[PDB]
Length: 129
Image (tube, rainbow, N blue to C red; front, side, top):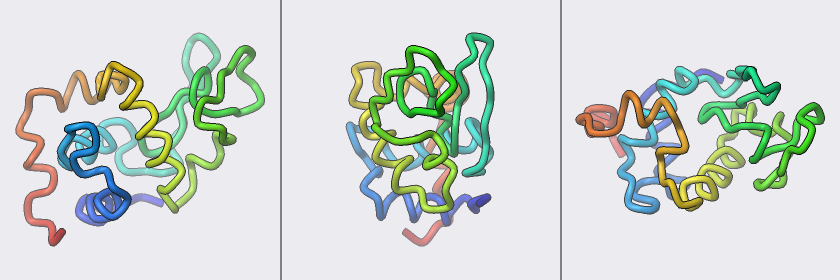
């Protein structure tokens, strides 16, 4: 499913992401925009053989099991296909584990490179939340 900007914001808020670990809603929406273009079905394979899945592009080497990443840790205890669902619940629960991992949102390279230090509030402007 390809979410609309305000639709995703509303779903993320309802799921407890607004200000989770100090990160305002605009941060999460900006990250999803640049990680997957708001598409739950996005996948991207990496040079090391691992693959990133979903709206927030979580890596199969640490977060989920895709059955083809030797040495994968599966810290969110879910098959990677779960992250591609139209229901963002699994993606949200896993994201909460990741952001609490110590590096905060820097775990998402697109966030670090294109959201961090910008007017992230712009991402939720105009939305009825």
